[PDB]
Length: 292
Length: 6
Image 1 (tube, rainbow over the protein chains, first blue to last red):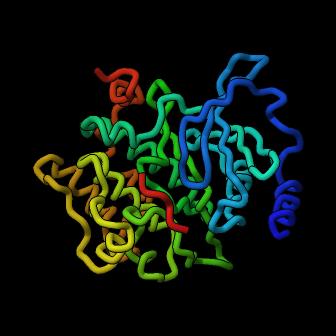
Image 2 (cartoon, rainbow over the protein chains, first blue to last red):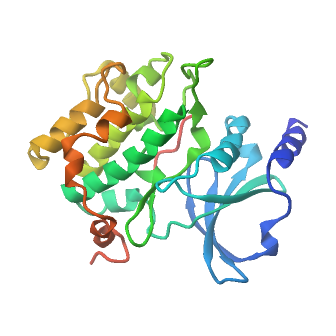
């Protein structure tokens, strides 16, 4: 009943039609935030596209599904996954989008060790994206290695906007408890009104992922890790000797508890650590199809 | 992987 009501609303917003008419050989590759991701073959071209499938009945907050359409209609960018078309297919929202065939940053972080040319390239790419989103008041709210995707030639793109929200003069802060526990900003876990600064902290946790292979407290149940994040000093790297003073100085601007003192994305683009970033080619050897 | 909390 409110499901039927919701299918009808989504219908007025999405493209008409059914992309099964032009797509073949759907193969599941992933499950993430809000549903599954398949690759599919575009019949007329032989090209490959990704299809995000999101069951309306399985969302904590169905209304966040509109985020997939807002972000597509409005915030395209070099470092953001491009979204082609959305559809309602029975009880699911489908988004046909760019296939990032290099896979997710998670698979690199859990299986090899990045150097700082590589970390700087990822950080620079992510920060360019955030600088542009944050200037327009868009907060991603689920920054983590699982949300950073790569092309085969090593270009880095932000993905998975399903949890994002907007701030503006009339709604200067968000309040919702949203993200993935281990990456959540402290002010967000403490239920304070928050803004784009939350993505900056989450990026810091992603830097810890890149250096250590895991975010802090990863061995704790989620609820206990949030409590630890709320109450404790900023989390530390397992091994500080494994980062340069430059990388350490960079991280220290990210993992600041007071969001007013945390660096913005605009400021971070100017940080000397980013001078280390290699081109996309430098990221390539890290991917599963290339490492030994 | 840990799931998002909404």
